Amino acid sequence: VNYTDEETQKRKKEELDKLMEPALGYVTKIPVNIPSVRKTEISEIDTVTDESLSLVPNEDKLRTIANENYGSVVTKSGSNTMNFVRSGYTIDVVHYGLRDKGYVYYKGVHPSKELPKGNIIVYQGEWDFTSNADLDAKRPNYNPEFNGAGAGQRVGVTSADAKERTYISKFNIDFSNKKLNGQLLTKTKENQEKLRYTVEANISGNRFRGKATATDKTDPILGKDSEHLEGGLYGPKSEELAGKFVAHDKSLFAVFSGKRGNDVLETVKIIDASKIDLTTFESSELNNFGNANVLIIDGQKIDLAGADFKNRKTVDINGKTMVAIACCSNLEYMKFGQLWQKEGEQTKDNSLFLQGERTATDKIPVGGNYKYVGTWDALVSKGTNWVAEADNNRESGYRSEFDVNFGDKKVSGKLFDKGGIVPVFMINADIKGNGFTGTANTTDTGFALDSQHGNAVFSDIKVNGGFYGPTAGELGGQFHHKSDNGSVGAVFGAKRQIEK
């Protein structure tokens, strides 16, 4: 007697919804019937959190079982075609019995921060799948598409088990409308194509959510619809994509990849996510999927939302205990602050970070003058340390104030020390697209590190920033510099104002 958990129809839906959460990648186990049961659904769908394309998800765990049973592992990843994504399988091809057969996966690297500006862009690639296992269903003993007999009855069938067929994918991405359509086809040895799924999805950030409609509902294996297709663009300028879908009855798990051609396209920033190392004052990029209220550290999520003005978040990731101070509550489409690993009594690898969801270029105001008001975080190093930390005091806190002239395409900013009446930094930038670029300067004489005490002087430090939100109602930016006569790293964000 096989006793299992009674999963409500509600519970089943919620289960699939969790699979829609963006990630660098996903991997699944190929179902294998235990001798007791007759049906094994696709169940253990795990996220991929490692950031190296050479690492094949769970191949290590499979090679372990394979060697003991003297099996033979074969891996298909598309590594000879793709530069930023990997997809396919790792399979024990001489599999028999009840041991593990393998895994189906996709993973990607450098979640895209720039998309092509518009038009319809073709992406071509491949796809793969594993089915579930079901004795009490459909599947004929002879299946002209798959090698051998009984395919899909006691063990899940995969694209690896296909007879002289290739599995090709084609996508049209409408970047103007952030829509995506696609076809998943099979091609036989006689160059004859057969459509198996059509794909439709909506782009948000660098991710897409949608559905896969089965072409042939009489198909014993590839015949069920999916209301749960998710994937993402990868590569610095969306050179490639990858994703998955799960059939609504969990009878199929499919992965797909895609790569656009060599035609050079004009791109636009959709996402800002970078960090400044408060030791080297170098800037490095962070993974991000289009949500600025989520920080991705080692492929795992940290929620930055909170009830206070700024919030301290502590999450344990890969043994490393991380702490992030995220500001601010009044900013809906951006976050900035401090990031470090808690030694427990120190801080390891201190850094500042900036994240934001860029405004659409055609939604940047063509004219007008507005005031932006927020805070900032910084660190200055010249013998001793000078710090600025985010606060809620608009009067005499670590204020950040901006006048934006959209007509003259100009941004002018001032960063104040606490209690100060004169800014310590003055920002002068030019608005280009949905961002701005310029310089940060101290006064001729600078500002005291604190009450013979050395003080900081900085000339023409490069400033990078962007406008965030539907109508650019928020802005933020960063700058950093390393030298022997003083170093600095700063991040700031501000909210557009109205007059009462």
Image (cartoon, helix red, strand yellow):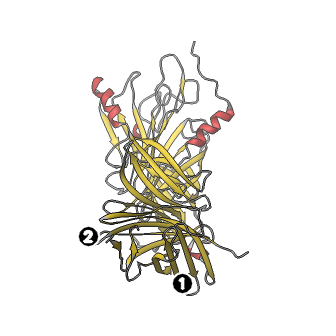
- Residue furthest toward the bottom? 408
Of the numbered discs 2 and 1, the one sitting upstream in the chain is 1
Check whether the beta carbons of the residues at disc 2 and disc 1 lie within 8 A of each other: no
Question: In this view of the protein, can residue 322 be seen by the observer?
Answer: yes
Q: Is residue 64 left or right of residue 330?
A: left
Identify the residue under disc 2: 484
- Residue 338, how many percent across, how many down? 45, 56
- Residue furthest toward the front? 452
Answer above or below: position of 202 versus 25. Answer: below
Q: What is the spatial separation of the Cα atoms under label 2 and label 1, in whole angstroms? A: 35 Å
Q: Crowdedness of circle 1 by 10 Å Cα count: few (<14), some, many (20+)?
A: some
Quadrant location of residue 405?
bottom right
Check the picture and name the quadrant holding the C terminus. bottom right
- Callout 2 amino acid: Asp
- Residue 141, how many percent across, how many down? 49, 27
Q: Is residue 396 left or right of residue 107?
A: right
What secondary structure is found at the residue carrying circle 2?
A: loop
Q: Which mark is residue 409?
A: 1
Answer above or below: position of 138 versus 193. Answer: above
- Callout 1 amino acid: Lys
Check the picture and name the quadrant holding the N terminus. top right
Q: Is residue 83 left or right of residue 193?
A: left
Answer above or below: position of 243 versus 275. Answer: above
What secondary structure is found at the residue carrying circle 1?
A: loop
